[PDB]
Length: 107
Length: 107
Ligand SMILES: [Zn+2]
Ligand SMILES: [Zn+2]
Ligand SMILES: [Zn+2]
Ligand SMILES: [Zn+2]
Image 1 (cartoon, chains in turn blue, green):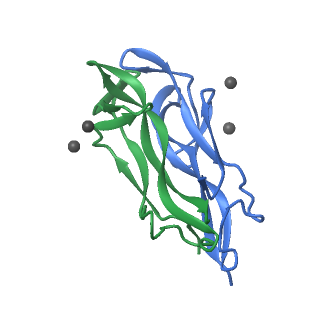
Image 2: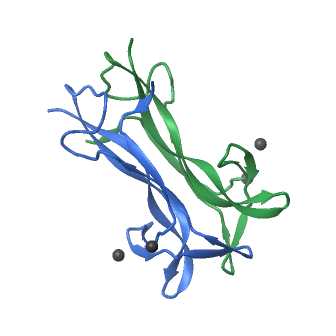
Image 3: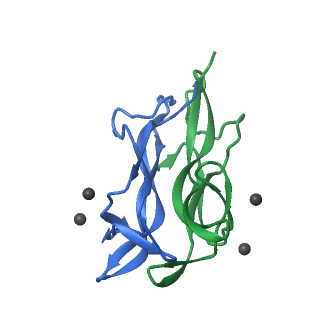
Protein backbone atom coordinates (compact mmCIF):
# COMPACT_ATOMS: atom_id res chain seq x y z
CA UNK A 1 0.00 0.00 0.00
CA UNK A 2 1.79 3.05 -1.31
CA UNK A 3 1.86 6.69 -0.21
CA UNK A 4 4.18 9.68 -0.13
CA UNK A 5 6.40 11.25 2.51
CA UNK A 6 4.26 14.37 2.82
CA UNK A 7 0.49 14.15 2.48
CA UNK A 8 -0.82 16.58 -0.10
CA UNK A 9 -4.14 17.91 -1.30
CA UNK A 10 -5.06 19.06 -4.80
CA UNK A 11 -7.99 21.20 -5.93
CA UNK A 12 -9.14 22.91 -9.09
CA UNK A 13 -9.62 26.69 -8.71
CA UNK A 14 -11.71 28.82 -11.11
CA UNK A 15 -12.46 31.85 -8.91
CA UNK A 16 -8.92 33.19 -8.97
CA UNK A 17 -8.44 36.94 -8.88
CA UNK A 18 -5.14 37.73 -7.19
CA UNK A 19 -1.85 36.00 -7.85
CA UNK A 20 1.84 36.52 -7.36
CA UNK A 21 3.81 36.96 -10.53
CA UNK A 22 7.11 35.51 -11.62
CA UNK A 23 9.25 38.08 -9.81
CA UNK A 24 7.34 38.39 -6.54
CA UNK A 25 4.70 41.02 -7.37
CA UNK A 26 0.95 40.78 -6.90
CA UNK A 27 -1.21 40.85 -10.04
CA UNK A 28 -4.89 40.58 -10.86
CA UNK A 29 -6.19 37.53 -12.68
CA UNK A 30 -9.08 38.14 -15.04
CA UNK A 31 -12.11 35.90 -15.09
CA UNK A 32 -12.31 35.15 -18.82
CA UNK A 33 -9.94 34.82 -21.79
CA UNK A 34 -10.17 35.22 -25.60
CA UNK A 35 -7.78 32.65 -27.18
CA UNK A 36 -7.97 32.31 -31.01
CA UNK A 37 -11.57 33.55 -31.36
CA UNK A 38 -13.20 31.76 -28.39
CA UNK A 39 -14.01 32.80 -24.80
CA UNK A 40 -12.66 30.57 -22.00
CA UNK A 41 -12.37 30.84 -18.25
CA UNK A 42 -9.01 30.52 -16.51
CA UNK A 43 -8.46 27.38 -14.42
CA UNK A 44 -5.56 26.21 -12.22
CA UNK A 45 -4.59 22.89 -10.63
CA UNK A 46 -3.05 23.59 -7.22
CA UNK A 47 -1.40 21.23 -4.72
CA UNK A 48 -0.56 22.28 -1.13
CA UNK A 49 0.89 20.45 1.85
CA UNK A 50 -1.51 19.10 4.46
CA UNK A 51 0.90 19.30 7.43
CA UNK A 52 3.50 22.04 6.89
CA UNK A 53 4.30 22.01 10.61
CA UNK A 54 7.96 22.96 10.98
CA UNK A 55 8.44 21.36 14.40
CA UNK A 56 6.43 18.09 14.57
CA UNK A 57 7.41 17.26 11.00
CA UNK A 58 4.75 16.02 8.67
CA UNK A 59 7.37 13.96 6.85
CA UNK A 60 6.68 10.24 7.25
CA UNK A 61 9.39 7.63 7.48
CA UNK A 62 12.66 9.51 8.18
CA UNK A 63 15.99 8.62 9.84
CA UNK A 64 15.04 11.14 12.53
CA UNK A 65 18.24 10.21 14.40
CA UNK A 66 20.48 11.83 11.77
CA UNK A 67 17.97 14.16 10.10
CA UNK A 68 15.53 17.06 10.55
CA UNK A 69 12.58 17.46 8.22
CA UNK A 70 9.48 19.43 7.27
CA UNK A 71 6.88 19.50 4.51
CA UNK A 72 6.88 22.43 2.09
CA UNK A 73 4.78 23.61 -0.85
CA UNK A 74 6.78 24.04 -4.04
CA UNK A 75 5.70 26.09 -7.03
CA UNK A 76 5.47 25.99 -10.78
CA UNK A 77 4.69 28.77 -13.21
CA UNK A 78 1.86 29.05 -15.69
CA UNK A 79 0.84 31.89 -17.94
CA UNK A 80 -2.40 33.74 -17.27
CA UNK A 81 -4.26 36.80 -18.49
CA UNK A 82 -3.52 39.47 -15.89
CA UNK A 83 -3.99 43.23 -15.73
CA UNK A 84 -1.08 45.49 -16.67
CA UNK A 85 -1.97 49.12 -16.18
CA UNK A 86 -5.43 48.50 -17.62
CA UNK A 87 -5.04 46.54 -20.72
CA UNK A 88 -4.24 42.90 -20.15
CA UNK A 89 -0.94 41.02 -20.20
CA UNK A 90 -0.08 37.36 -20.71
CA UNK A 91 2.25 36.81 -17.78
CA UNK A 92 3.66 33.97 -15.69
CA UNK A 93 2.16 33.54 -12.23
CA UNK A 94 3.41 31.29 -9.45
CA UNK A 95 1.11 28.49 -8.27
CA UNK A 96 1.34 25.79 -5.58
CA UNK A 97 2.15 22.57 -7.42
CA UNK A 98 3.30 19.93 -4.91
CA UNK A 99 4.40 19.06 -1.37
CA UNK A 100 7.98 17.83 -0.86
CA UNK A 101 10.01 16.98 2.25
CA UNK A 102 13.10 19.07 3.05
CA UNK A 103 16.01 17.90 5.22
CA UNK A 104 18.94 19.20 7.23
CA UNK A 105 21.43 17.04 9.15
CA UNK A 106 21.66 17.21 12.94
CA UNK A 107 24.56 18.83 14.86
CA UNK B 1 22.34 23.53 4.56
CA UNK B 2 18.97 22.50 3.22
CA UNK B 3 17.90 20.13 0.44
CA UNK B 4 15.08 17.78 -0.48
CA UNK B 5 14.57 14.03 -0.25
CA UNK B 6 14.65 13.53 -4.01
CA UNK B 7 16.93 15.65 -6.17
CA UNK B 8 15.03 17.31 -8.99
CA UNK B 9 15.76 19.28 -12.13
CA UNK B 10 13.65 22.00 -13.72
CA UNK B 11 13.79 23.40 -17.25
CA UNK B 12 11.77 25.74 -19.41
CA UNK B 13 10.53 24.14 -22.67
CA UNK B 14 9.38 26.14 -25.71
CA UNK B 15 9.79 23.55 -28.48
CA UNK B 16 6.88 21.39 -27.35
CA UNK B 17 4.88 19.59 -30.00
CA UNK B 18 3.47 16.40 -28.53
CA UNK B 19 1.79 16.07 -25.16
CA UNK B 20 -0.48 13.75 -23.27
CA UNK B 21 -3.89 15.13 -22.52
CA UNK B 22 -5.97 15.03 -19.38
CA UNK B 23 -7.41 11.57 -20.02
CA UNK B 24 -4.33 9.78 -21.33
CA UNK B 25 -4.41 10.60 -25.05
CA UNK B 26 -1.64 12.08 -27.16
CA UNK B 27 -2.24 15.54 -28.65
CA UNK B 28 -0.29 18.02 -30.74
CA UNK B 29 0.84 21.29 -29.21
CA UNK B 30 0.92 24.25 -31.56
CA UNK B 31 3.86 26.61 -31.67
CA UNK B 32 2.03 29.94 -31.33
CA UNK B 33 -1.14 31.30 -29.72
CA UNK B 34 -3.53 34.23 -30.30
CA UNK B 35 -4.82 35.40 -26.86
CA UNK B 36 -6.89 38.63 -26.85
CA UNK B 37 -5.42 40.10 -30.06
CA UNK B 38 -1.72 39.24 -29.55
CA UNK B 39 0.52 36.38 -30.74
CA UNK B 40 2.44 34.45 -28.06
CA UNK B 41 4.45 31.25 -27.96
CA UNK B 42 3.54 28.44 -25.57
CA UNK B 43 5.96 27.80 -22.69
CA UNK B 44 6.03 25.19 -19.91
CA UNK B 45 7.95 24.82 -16.64
CA UNK B 46 8.75 21.13 -16.12
CA UNK B 47 10.36 19.34 -13.16
CA UNK B 48 11.55 15.71 -13.34
CA UNK B 49 13.33 13.42 -10.91
CA UNK B 50 17.09 13.04 -11.24
CA UNK B 51 17.31 9.49 -9.80
CA UNK B 52 14.04 7.60 -10.37
CA UNK B 53 15.85 4.31 -9.72
CA UNK B 54 13.32 1.92 -8.20
CA UNK B 55 15.87 -0.35 -6.53
CA UNK B 56 18.79 1.77 -5.19
CA UNK B 57 16.35 4.46 -4.06
CA UNK B 58 17.18 8.04 -4.80
CA UNK B 59 15.36 9.07 -1.63
CA UNK B 60 17.79 10.57 0.88
CA UNK B 61 17.44 10.17 4.62
CA UNK B 62 14.93 7.34 5.18
CA UNK B 63 14.26 4.83 7.99
CA UNK B 64 15.34 2.14 5.52
CA UNK B 65 14.91 -0.45 8.28
CA UNK B 66 11.11 -0.09 8.30
CA UNK B 67 10.57 1.46 4.86
CA UNK B 68 11.04 1.08 1.10
CA UNK B 69 11.28 4.14 -1.13
CA UNK B 70 11.72 5.55 -4.61
CA UNK B 71 11.63 8.90 -6.37
CA UNK B 72 8.76 9.63 -8.76
CA UNK B 73 7.72 12.45 -11.09
CA UNK B 74 4.29 13.85 -10.30
CA UNK B 75 2.17 15.87 -12.68
CA UNK B 76 0.04 18.97 -12.88
CA UNK B 77 -2.26 20.13 -15.63
CA UNK B 78 -2.13 23.29 -17.68
CA UNK B 79 -4.21 24.40 -20.63
CA UNK B 80 -2.61 24.65 -24.06
CA UNK B 81 -3.62 25.24 -27.65
CA UNK B 82 -3.74 21.77 -29.21
CA UNK B 83 -5.10 20.35 -32.44
CA UNK B 84 -8.59 18.82 -32.45
CA UNK B 85 -9.43 17.39 -35.84
CA UNK B 86 -7.83 20.39 -37.54
CA UNK B 87 -9.07 23.44 -35.86
CA UNK B 88 -7.52 24.08 -32.49
CA UNK B 89 -8.76 23.33 -28.98
CA UNK B 90 -7.90 24.80 -25.59
CA UNK B 91 -7.31 21.63 -23.61
CA UNK B 92 -5.57 20.47 -20.44
CA UNK B 93 -2.29 18.63 -20.90
CA UNK B 94 -0.31 16.76 -18.27
CA UNK B 95 3.18 18.04 -17.44
CA UNK B 96 5.96 16.90 -15.08
CA UNK B 97 5.82 19.26 -12.12
CA UNK B 98 7.88 17.82 -9.25
CA UNK B 99 9.78 14.86 -7.76
CA UNK B 100 8.40 13.28 -4.57
CA UNK B 101 9.44 10.24 -2.54
CA UNK B 102 7.00 7.31 -2.24
CA UNK B 103 7.06 4.71 0.55
CA UNK B 104 5.83 1.23 1.40
CA UNK B 105 6.45 -0.57 4.70
CA UNK B 106 8.57 -3.72 4.84
CA UNK B 107 7.16 -7.25 5.43
ZN1 LIG C 1 -15.23 34.69 -6.33
ZN1 LIG D 1 -3.68 41.69 -2.63
ZN1 LIG E 1 11.80 21.67 -32.33
ZN1 LIG F 1 3.50 10.53 -30.58
